[PDB]
């Protein structure tokens, strides 16, 4: 469409093109807000997004930390203060998940003080 070239040409895929790397906006002791710009369709439309997180000091796994996200800006919650986190965004469609976004790179939560200062 409004482009017609890329480095590669086609794929063996029926999935959306992935989101951009998220940003980070609001953070607290245990919520943080992520903002990204969306993927684009091809074969099919998009259904929703996921966000995963990973933290060595939480569980050794990547886990789902929001599911069927219908927005581009999302407050994560329930985290641990003074703990590092990673995030990736994933698109969803009628056939699979897309390729992931880039990682957010490791945020740190604040602390469970009030931050009067």
Image (spheres, grey):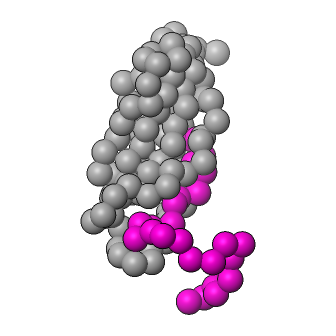
Q: Residue at x 44, y 25 (%)?
A: 61
Q: Residue at x 47, y 48 (%)?
A: 89
Q: Residue at x 41, y 66 (%)?
A: 15
Quadrant of the frame with the C terminus: top right
Membership of 8 in magenta stretch: yes
The one nearer the camera, 84 or 115, is 84
Boundaries of the magenta span = 1-25
Q: Where on the picture, by quarter, is residue 77?
A: top left
Q: Position of residue 48 (x, y in %)?
A: 33, 59
Q: Position of residue 27 (x, y in %)?
A: 53, 31
Quadrant of the frame with the N terminus: bottom right
Q: Residue at x 63, y 85 (%)?
A: 3
- Furthest toward the front, the residue is 12
- Furthest toward the right, the residue is 7
Q: Position of residue 58 (x, y in %)?
A: 45, 16
Q: Where on the picture, by quarter, is residue 64?
A: top left
Q: Position of residue 4 (x, y in %)?
A: 64, 87
The one nearer the camera, 106 or 115, is 106
The one nearer the camera, 27 or 20, is 20
Magenta: main secondary structure:
loop
Residue 34 visible in the displayed image: yes
Membership of 82 in magenta stretch: no
């Amino acid at each position: 469409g409004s482009s017609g070239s890329s480095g590669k040409n086609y794929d063996l895929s029926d999935l959306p093109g992935p989101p951009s790397k998220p940003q980070v906006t609001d953070v607290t002791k245990n919520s943080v807000t992520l903002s990204w710009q969306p993927g684009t369709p091809g074969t099919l439309p998009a259904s929703a997004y996921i966000i995963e997180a990973f933290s060595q000091s939480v569980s050794n796994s990547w886990q789902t930390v929001a599911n069927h996200v219908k927005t581009t800006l999302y407050t994560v919650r329930g985290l641990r203060p003074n703990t590092i986190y990673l995030f990736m965004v994933r698109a969803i469609n009628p056939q699979g998940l897309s390729d992931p976004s880039p990682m957010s790179d490791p945020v740190r939560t604040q602390d469970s003080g009030p931050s009067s200062g």
